Amino acid sequence: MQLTPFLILLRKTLEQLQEKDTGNIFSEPVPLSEVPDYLDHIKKPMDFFTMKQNLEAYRYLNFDDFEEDFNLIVSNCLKYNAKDTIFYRAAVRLREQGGAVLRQARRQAEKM
Ligand SMILES: CC(=O)c1c(C)[nH]c(-c2csc(N3CCNCC3)n2)c1CCC(C)C
C-alpha cells in the first residue's frame, strides 16, 4: 500500500489510544529520576510521546510494529506495578479499550 495514508491512519490511531489514557500516565516516559528501580526489570520503556517520535521518524511501516510498542506500554505497567494499584488497573483498562481501537484500525489498514 501507499505510505502517506498509512501514516495518517497511524496518527489517528495513536491519538485515539492517547485519548483512552485519561490520566495521561502513559503520555511521556516514566520519570526514571523518580523511579530508580524502574529499569531493574523493565527492558524497554515505552510511552505515547516516544511512539509519536517513532511514527514521525518512519519507524512504523506496518501495523504490528506500532502495536508492539503499544503493547509495551501496557505490559511494562502491569509488570512494574502491584495488582492492587491504580496504575495496574489503568493498564488493564488501556489494554481493553486500546485493543478495540487497534482492531478497528487494522480493519481500516486491511482495506487499503
Ligand atoms: C511506574 C509506572 O508505571 C508509571 C507510569 C505508567 N507513569 C508514571 C508517572 C508519570 S509522572 C510520575 N511522577 C511525577 C510526580 N511524582 C511521582 C512520579 N510518574 C509512573 C511512575 C509512578 C511511580 C512514581 C509510583
Image (spheres, rainbow, N blue to C red):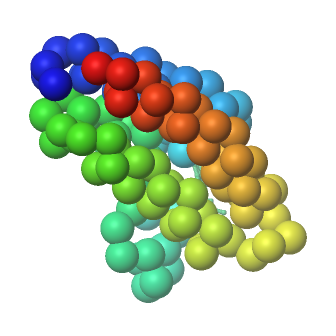
* Quadrant position of residue 77: bottom right
Give 71 or 80, whichever is nearer the viewer.
71
Horizontal arrangement in the rendering, residue 54 relative to residue 103 (left or right): left
- Residue 95 appears at what percent x and percent y? 64, 51
Q: Is residue 69 above or below residue 49?
A: below
* Quadrant position of residue 45: bottom left
Q: How many marks?
A: 0
Residue at the far bottom in the pictured view: 40
Split into 4 quadrants, where in the image is the N terminus? Answer: top left
| Residue at 61% over, 25% down | 19
| Residue at 52% over, 37% down | 102
| Residue at 60% over, 74% down | 80
Question: Do we see residue 18 in this rendering?
Answer: no
- Residue 61 appears at what percent x and percent y? 18, 38
Horizontal arrangement in the rendering, residue 71 relative to residue 43 (left or right): right
Give 108 or 14, whichever is nearer the viewer.
108
| Residue at 33% over, 49% down | 64
Question: Do we see residue 83 in this rendering?
Answer: yes
- Residue 4 appears at what percent x and percent y? 17, 15
Q: Is residue 99 above or below residue 108?
A: below
Q: Is residue 65 above or below residue 54?
A: below
Split into 4 quadrants, where in the image is the C terminus? Answer: top left
- Residue 10 appears at what percent x and percent y? 35, 27
